[PDB]
Length: 303
Length: 5
Image (tube, rainbow over all chains, first blue to last red; front, side, top):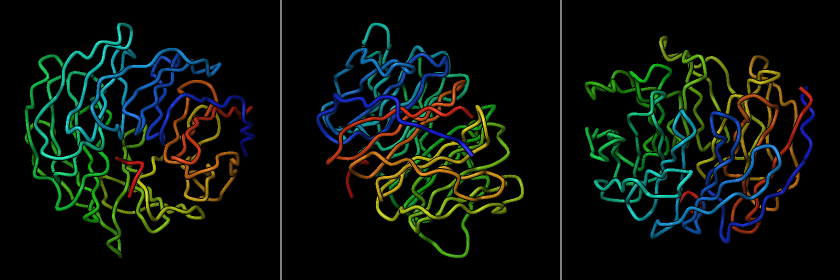
């Protein structure tokens, strides 16, 4: 089992934190917030680095380019913004969604961005030009998450409409719709690091690992509280192979991926833990919490 | 935003 212990608490956002993400090169943590700001923090020491500003309304998600140089953020102002982290400049403002933008990611290559919106679509954008390339009529309710697979050829999306769908990046065609025996809102999805699986959260307090190719649910993770918020979930891969997620009882849950047992619960936050991220090389977890808390915490384990 | 609803 891991032994995550609290190392730093990061204060600075003035409203609920919405997402935290570690840069691929391991140097930085980025955070986004309902306060319309992105903040950068040292990944190892928690030291505040800088604030990146410009959105007109709250931000629900932020994501790093694979070279750790750029961020993309998704906002209630109905835009995404692409940022040069070093200069703090907004390179492009991506206009096209007709309602709040909720989720975003670059492809592993980092020439494309995928976004999901309250407008029920998924859009794919050219990073260099900031132009929308394709609009997929993906869902019949808000899109909660979007993620590219390992080679960028597929996109997975999830929605309040109860579906996870997998899309061909190049053609835009729907290649698969995944749903289990009940239809709760799907609140998060992402491909596994090896690209074989999809990890999906549903708003019935459940995480599931699906074999994408087979269209089969292989593992269920339960024990946490998740009925209300779109809480991120992670694969922790630096030490033991875990699944990590925030929870609506203000804890971070960690499960053994293979056995599905809870291996640790991290206590310390004073509101719902909406987002967690796992460092790419060290056994470090960042967690972020909602309006009554407003902090980010860094936890470290020996394994 | 994600921090509501």
